[PDB]
Length: 264
Ligand SMILES: COc1cc(CCc2ccccc2)c(C(=O)O)c(O)c1CC=C(C)C
Image (spheres, rainbow, N blue to C red):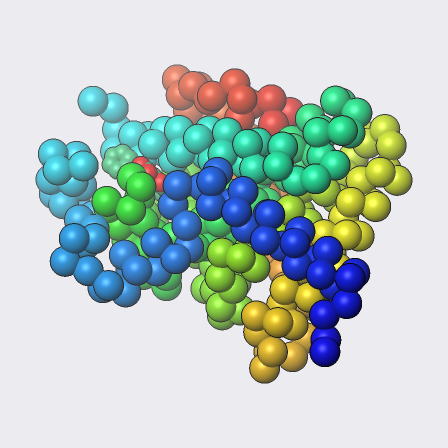
C-alpha cells in the first residue's frame, strides 16, 4: 500500500490546513464557483455592468464612482488581510517564529495571497463582490477613468491563467501556506526556521496534488511557476498606488494597507 508514516503525517497536515482555511475564509472557491456557474436560484448575484446597474446595485446590495469602487476594494483587502492573518496563525510553527519575522512574512505575503484567492472569485467576464451577492464586469471596471480603469486588468489576466489549473480549496489551503512561509522575504532575521516549515508545506502540497490531481502532470511545478505571476502583479499594483497618491491627494488609504506598502 502507498501510505507510509511520513506520507501519513503530510496527509494530516493537509487536512489541518484545509480545516483552518474553511474556518478563516467565509467565501471559498467552492461557494464562488457555485454562485458563478448557476448551482442556483438562491445564490444568483446582482450584476453591475454600467452606471445605472451600479446605482441599482447600491440599492439592493457620494463621491466619484471610480473612487467609491476603489475604496470598496480597499476595505475588502483589509478584511482579507485579517482573514489571512487568522489563517497564518494556524500554520504549524508560524506563531513560534520571532515576532518580527511573523510581521515580515505577513507584510510581503498577504498581497500575493489576496490575488491568489481573488482568482477564485473571477472568471474571464468579471468578479464576485460583496460576499458573492454581486458581480462587477471586467468591461465596467476597465471603463473607469484613468488611472482606476486599469487597476483590475492584470488581476483578471492572472486569474484566467491561474484558474486553468483547476485547483480546489484543499489545494489552495496548502499553496497559500507555502506562500506565507517564504524564507526569501526581505529583512528576515532567522531564515532557517521558516525554510524548515516551508519544506514541510512543500512536501504536503506535492502529495496533495499527486493524490487530488493524478492525471495532471507536473501540476506541482506549474503551480510553483505561478508565484512569478503573483510577484509581478504585486509590483505593478504598488506602482499604480504611487500614481494614485499623487493625482488623488484627497483620497485616504487604510493605514494597515499603507504599512504593508511601506518600502515593499
Ligand atoms: C473591484 O474589486 C472589488 C470591488 C468591490 C467594491 C464594489 C462596489 C463599490 C462601491 C459601489 C458599488 C460597488 C468589492 C466589494 O464591495 O466586495 C470587492 O469585493 C472587490 C474585489 C476585490 C478585491 C478582493 C481586491
